[PDB]
Length: 150
Ligand SMILES: [Ca+2]
Ligand SMILES: [Ca+2]
Ligand SMILES: [Ca+2]
Ligand SMILES: [Ca+2]
Ligand SMILES: [Ca+2]
Ligand SMILES: [Ca+2]
Ligand SMILES: [Ca+2]
Ligand SMILES: [Ca+2]
Ligand SMILES: [Mg+2]
Ligand SMILES: [Mg+2]
Image (cartoon, rainbow, N blue to C red):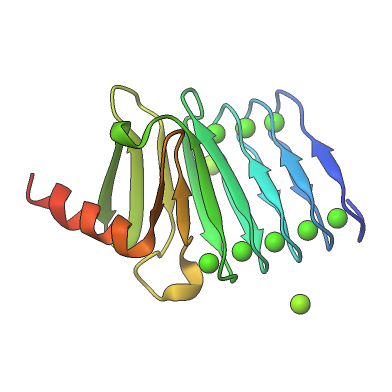
């Protein structure tokens, strides 16, 4: 990684990838990775394996989808973070687990957890972009409330 925009590409093992400043792309590959966007607007994709994703400050994009395993987002700041899930919104479940938000793809064991979502706004992502539609924070909370009474 460098202060410039980098494309950081892991391998099938457990990799640590730190983007540093600049608007980076982090592709972990298989294995259980640690990905840090740091400063800047970063795109993080843990891919297969159970990954820890730290977008950092700035407006970060997290990818998720079928076969991505159990990944955990640890946010730090930014008013325009996004999760881009390669599935229809009609296949997403939302639940509060402790202080975390858990997002599941129905029919799979792929699960994305936002650590400490419910602690304060700096831990949150602001939009979920599914294949067909976008869901904002008020929308995510309505889904969590609806799904908890399901
Ligand atoms: Ca960066
Ligand atoms: Ca960089
Ligand atoms: Ca890897
Ligand atoms: Ca991985
Ligand atoms: Ca960042
Ligand atoms: Ca961020
Ligand atoms: Ca993963
Ligand atoms: Ca945020
Ligand atoms: Mg700064
Ligand atoms: Mg782990």
